[PDB]
Image: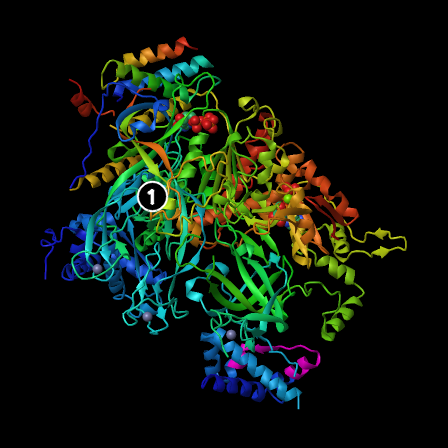
Amino acid sequence: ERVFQISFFNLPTVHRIRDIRSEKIGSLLSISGTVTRTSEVRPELYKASFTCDMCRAIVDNVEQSFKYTEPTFCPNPSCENRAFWTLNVTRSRFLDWQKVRIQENANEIPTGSMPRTLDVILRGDSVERAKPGDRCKFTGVEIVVPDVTQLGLPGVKPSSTLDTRGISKTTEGLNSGVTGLRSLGVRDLTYKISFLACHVISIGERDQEVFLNSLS
Amino acid sequence: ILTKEARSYLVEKYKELRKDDASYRITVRQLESMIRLSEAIARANCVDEITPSFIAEAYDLLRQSI
Amino acid sequence: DDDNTEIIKSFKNFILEFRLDSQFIYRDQLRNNILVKNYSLTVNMEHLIGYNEDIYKKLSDEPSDIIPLFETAITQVAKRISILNSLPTFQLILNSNANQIPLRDLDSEHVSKIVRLSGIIISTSVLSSRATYLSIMCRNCRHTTSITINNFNVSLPRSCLSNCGPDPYIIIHESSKFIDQQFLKLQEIPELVPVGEMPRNLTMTCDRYLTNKVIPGTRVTIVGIYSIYNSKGSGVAIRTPYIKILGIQSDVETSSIWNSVTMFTEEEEEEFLQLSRNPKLYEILTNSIAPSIFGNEDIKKAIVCLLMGGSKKILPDGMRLRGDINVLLLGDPGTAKSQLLKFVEKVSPIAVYTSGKGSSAAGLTASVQRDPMTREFYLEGGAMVLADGGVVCIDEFDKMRDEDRVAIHEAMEQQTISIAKAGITTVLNSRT
Amino acid sequence: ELTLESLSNVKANSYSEWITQPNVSRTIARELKSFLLEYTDETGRSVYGARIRTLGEMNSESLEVNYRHLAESKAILALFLAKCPEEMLKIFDLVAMEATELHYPDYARIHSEIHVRISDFPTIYSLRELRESNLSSLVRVTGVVTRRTGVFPQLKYVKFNCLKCGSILGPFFQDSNEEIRISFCTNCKSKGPFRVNGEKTVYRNYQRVTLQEAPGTVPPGRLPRHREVILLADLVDVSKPGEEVEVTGIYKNNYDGNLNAKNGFPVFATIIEANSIKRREGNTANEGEEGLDVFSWTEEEEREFRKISRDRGIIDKIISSMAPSIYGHRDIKTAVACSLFGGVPKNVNGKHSIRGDINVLLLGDPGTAKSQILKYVEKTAHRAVFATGQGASAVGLTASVRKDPITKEWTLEGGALVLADKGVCLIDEFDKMNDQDRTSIHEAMEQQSISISKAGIVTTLQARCSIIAAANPNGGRYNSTLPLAQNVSLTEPILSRFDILCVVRDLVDEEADERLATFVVDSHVRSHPELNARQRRLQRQRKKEEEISPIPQELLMKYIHYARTKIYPKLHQMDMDKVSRVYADLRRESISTGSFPITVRHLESILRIAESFAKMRLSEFVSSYDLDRAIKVVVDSFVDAQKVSVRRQLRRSFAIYTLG
Ligand SMILES: Nc1ncnc2c1ncn2[C@@H]1O[C@H](COP(=O)(O)OP(=O)(O)OP(=O)(O)O)[C@@H](O)[C@H]1O
Ligand SMILES: Nc1ncnc2c1ncn2[C@@H]1O[C@H](COP(=O)(O)OP(=O)(O)OP(=O)(O)O)[C@@H](O)[C@H]1O
Ligand SMILES: [Mg+2]
Ligand SMILES: [Zn+2]
Ligand SMILES: [Zn+2]
Ligand SMILES: [Zn+2]
């Protein structure tokens, strides 16, 4: 089946990057900004499929939110199993994924200002439609992204937040992190605001036979 | 494309220009540029064949700048 | 154990029953080595093939497993022919005449097989310690134990012998025995590198009586085993190859420290003194310098004088006088100036050939580098450090940059290099 | 059993499962074997039988199969190979080995498996346009090699041992990108420690490389993209750091924890397992031609070489075929041909090395097609490098020293003269160049080596390269009333290293101008862009080559490569007195009246040119005609670089030697 997408446009009012508050999280918005960095078109895991190690039973359509999620309770028999699955990478569905960095326009920047930034996520057919240096108007939903490293990623590769640079001492303990959840353990979960975009617009052949076709 | 008489007119004009120069300023590149100008002038008139009048116009344009 | 005993017996019979003409060569070599405190034995593979082909076939397919059995056979024979016991396990050194394999032809087909190859030494590491006899004690019950290790690639037992912990055992460092380990780096012969490829390097390990035997820049021939060790590079299940040295042949007679002693048997000394008495030795030596170059007799005489060198004197007041000769050739193109420089490189026992265009002061005298692991600064040698006690041939000398050329002033006359960089202040010797 | 008609209908809703079924995989193997055995081209000769015959001779481990051949007949198998490479390749390797064991029985003692290399895949992608729809499919991607890991052994059949049950597990085929994961015992019935089963195992050669996008492909002003490529056994060390390559392979995906941790979404890593490699460094003939190497020959082509090599006047046709569309300048063409074929290097008793390559210099007036000749030489040469003027540096034409990003040790990197080892380096506008950059090639031009002493690295490299240079005279134009030394800025040390010097003069002449203009206009007329049609294209493109080329260019490239690779002529019987007299006369007539430096270095160029002319004929011995022709070339190269006052006397004085 074709994973469908719905693209909204022509919203009444447009927002700037400095109007982004947490009270619009989950709402449909439109924003404007200048693109300054784009990444590769990576494949994102959409509908996962696994096989039980012992039964060989097949599970399909396991939704994933922000981290690699395997199924829990086994399928149709008596077999008891909490883990040890094998992803069937061939059966699983994937999608295109891209991350772009944008900053404020030259006019919205005050007289003395260090420009604010944001992370916009393009997915599906909207990849590569924003090029660095251009001025583009995005529209989508404002979301919040947690730190998955302290959410217990399967591999040892995360290695509990390995770092190369020193974090800010000013916001050490000032950034309010929630605790209590069993998956976290004694850890503290943190959040940051990002944007997810569904529609992108920009606001800033010598063959005779094919040429005659286009014109009215 | 180039016709039969166009080639003869082109070689005659190149020979005349080389004679008038005397090799200090005129080379093969001038003949190639004259061919290019003739083709462009032909593209202007929306014609797929080149007439010696076009070569005469290109020759006049080359002479006006030397 | 029912096959190892027969293998040891076969080796001991080989040692004790091999004879050519009227002399047991391998029985006599052991006794001669024991007298001068050399605990080793050198065996030629052709003799082993001639004696019995099954014994050779056993060794050729399982070297790391068979070689220690020959090692213990040698020391069993030694205690019989020397004693009616501070004799350590002997060493086996092998000689081969098989075809030489290039470094770039070594691959997965040659794992766990004895190979023969040649290359250039570029670096020698420092000596390290490896344990052979380990005295062991437990942390709780506290009883003595011992372990014996051979260096042909072990850990302390993950248990207890007689509650004690998982693997409780500590090493009693006194009453433990150790040997000498060294690491060397190899490189391809410059003329055997394929087209458009840069030369590649390889790692070798030597033990005991094969340490301090080569110096950087030497051309050698190596007989050893091609093996791999798992370590550490994002590849899956990949290993790093290296070579364990079994035999070394070196062109330069000089050892690591160049003992300044004679390494010449009387059969060669007689030849040399007979040569020295030739009334026309000067002409013979002159004619031997580049026989493919016409004329230029005085330059060849000067080259001979440079090769022999003068005398060096030390005075009571600490003065040092230079005893080396420097030569400059400033001439017209096409006069064979650059075909003599490369000949002097070949003839000289120690010599380096460099170009003035592609050079620098750090590369010529000495450099200072940072160790990725220790993160400190150490000194690394250069062209004038490698070519110590030899000759350096600098071509295109007029094209040198004026900053790089002035760094040679002290080395040319005072024969020392002074470094005062990054907390390191030393003076290194350089007699070239 | 099934039939080729029955493979059209598919079941299991997936092509991979349809292919891997036992009944389908028996028809596929038979059809592939029939294709291997029974395919014939237009001339009626089976090509794959000849390739298999050559495979055993060369002790090769790989077979090259063209995609067009397998698509023209049995197109369903072509589609299956296009969509599902991994399962098709396992079967096709087995059938290839079975076909190989019909010409060389007992070949399993040399090599145990035969690998298949696919060629001429129709669709070519760029690294920028790779998406998720290309996952697990065969792709063709062009790029530039940047960094190479090096060769390490890798496990092939992985084994495990469990201690409490002492169980030995069956061999496992490693994915080469994912570690073999086993936790269940067939005997122990529970979790147990697993060893690697030390010793008694089979290894393969493994290497990894990074491909960036080529600067030409990248849009102007945008950042390039890169990907990772895994090279298995028989494919290691083929590509070198700095070259531009085209790789056919399989596009795969894998799960990475760090990628999911940093980005924050369940994204996957991608990598390409290389199947075929084709070099495109210096090649502009990629517009046509079929295969992985267009400089390699077959048996019938070698027989045709030996057939056309015994015709009288082969040298004249070879010279006439150099740059056919350029009119005149036959001495330049002769010098270019002599440089292209080359001489023979020598070593006397292992202590005296003699160079065997010819260097050429072109000094001429503007507008005389020197650069076009350099471009033609770049196209025809097997290995070619191009540089111009101020765009090259001292270490850009030589070896440079860089800190390795991984090992963090000073290392050597290549340059223009090293990339063109056993090739040709071309330097356009050789007089508009810094002296410090120009003087870097002094060692490489004669000694054919590069010596570096920097940062603890003391090494000597090898650059067996030939140099063809083009320059402009002082004032832009040549004064025929002055000697050479006052028409150029170069001194004797660099002028002596050149073998052939061609002075190109533009003079006023009505008939010559008329002929040149007629030729140029006809050339522009010819080059205007306005059974199977794909062979009608070939015959039409051959008809245009008929007029101005005695032999086709594709044949000539393989001819030059074969001649350089195989032939090594000698100089047993020759006239020493004539050469000695010529050298003495040339030396005498230089200091007396001349400004062209002649040393012993010019005596050897005559012998090199004689050996080159011998190579042109595919002969193993130099004759008298070749030596006389070399003497004539050298004499004509010296007489025509004089003043107009003494040229007539010098030509008459030197005319006795070139009687023929
Ligand atoms: N006297 C000679 N005998 C034999 N060969 C000679 C003689 N003089 C020159 N040659 C030959 O001339 C060629 C070039 O000589 P070489 O490379 O040594 O020049 P050079 O003196 O270093 O020149 P440059 O000053 O240009 O660097 C070599 O092939 C060399 O064998
Ligand atoms: N017989 C010919 N002689 C000269 N030029 C020719 C000839 N036939 C064609 N041409 C054309 O004349 C033009 C001049 O050639 P080109 O650009 O190589 O000259 P150049 O002065 O040698 O170049 P450069 O300064 O780049 O080295 C080219 O377009 C070439 O194709
Ligand atoms: Mg020289
Ligand atoms: Zn189950
Ligand atoms: Zn204990
Ligand atoms: Zn078990």
- Spot occupied by residue A108 in the image (x, y as percentages of width and height): 39, 18
Q: Could one spot residue A136 in this view of the protein?
A: no
Q: Nearer the viewer, residue C428 or C139?
A: C139
- Spot occupied by residue D563 in the image (x, y as percentages of width and height): 42, 50
C415 shown above or below C160: above
C69 shown above or below D433: below
Residue C128 is a magenta residue: no
Q: Could one spot residue D620 in this view of the protein?
A: yes
**Extreme-top residue of the structure:** B64
Residue at disc 1, CB closer than 8 Å to ligand 2 = no
Residue C34 is a magenta residue: yes
Q: How many numbered circles are shown?
A: 1
Left or right: D41 with respect to C14? Answer: left
- Magenta-tinted stretch: C29-48
For mark 1, give the secondary structure. Answer: helix
Q: Amino acid at mark 1?
A: Glu
- Spot occupied by residue C253 in the image (x, y as percentages of width and height): 68, 66
Q: Which residue is mark 1?
A: D554
C298 shown above or below A108: below
Q: Nearer the viewer, residue D624 or D399?
A: D399
- Spot occupied by residue A35 in the image (x, y as percentages of width and height): 36, 27
Left or right: D84 with respect to D636? Answer: left
Is the image coloured rainbow, by chain, by secondary structure, or in one colour? rainbow
